[PDB]
Image 1 (cartoon, protein in one colour):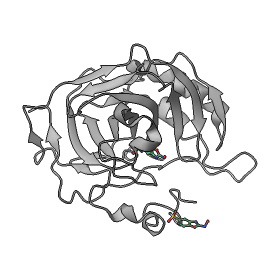
Image 2 (cartoon, helix red, strand yellow):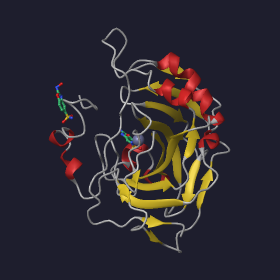
Image 3 (cartoon, helix red, strand yellow):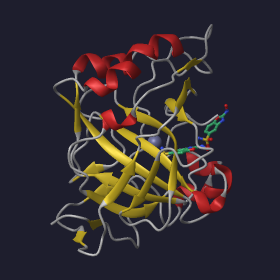
Image 4 (cartoon, protein in one colour):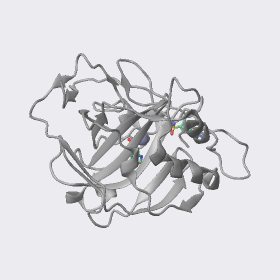
Length: 257
Ligand SMILES: NS(=O)(=O)c1ccc2o/c(=N/O)[nH]c2c1
Ligand SMILES: NS(=O)(=O)c1ccc2o/c(=N\O)[nH]c2c1
Ligand SMILES: [Zn+2]
């Protein structure tokens, strides 16, 4: 149903998901001069050493690398967060051209892609309950710029041939998501939403200041994926990003000055 085309894209989503016009929608433009440094924000705690990746799935909108979230194996804590959030999956949003693709923007600048490491608050028991709560999710967002290759990403790139079309999945064990992080964990944070339907307003967004660099060949391989299923007309999976939404009554906070 919904997607990213002329006839089903972000400007249409509000007709089935009226919260698309809500008070805390994501993504947003991060105006760096307007964000407020909050010296009481704690450093992020990323504990991924016990992460257990399971599978990679083309869901028709992006690809998801899924993790075992039945125990506290890969968790995000600290920063603006209270409690413990478990990593359930990561995915990306990217463009058809290197000058677009990210969901968040920084002083209106678009990056080539954006990584979302999705975590849910363990006090709610399961991801489906968590998305119903204003503090249910924490998504760690990391920008990708085109330049040198990111070695930690290559294993992802290399399996994409096996999940070209919607509904395909492949075993994807022993992937270490720590290899996708930049050096610095300086971040901006604001309350927001899922950036795809159902657009639920359940996300504490934590967007890293420092982008990672990926090579032109790496992002080109993202762009060879397909939104369609096998045996349907080929539509390249590109430009699967929602544009920046109004900030409304929200202040973006920075962990760094
Ligand atoms: N984007 S949305 O509100 O879920 C949307 C927009 C246009 C649509 O056309 C449809 N017939 O296949 N479904 C649909 C959903
Ligand atoms: N793109 S996003 O805001 O990180 C995100 C994260 C988890 C999600 O689950 C979804 N369907 O149940 N959509 C979705 C978007
Ligand atoms: Zn996302």
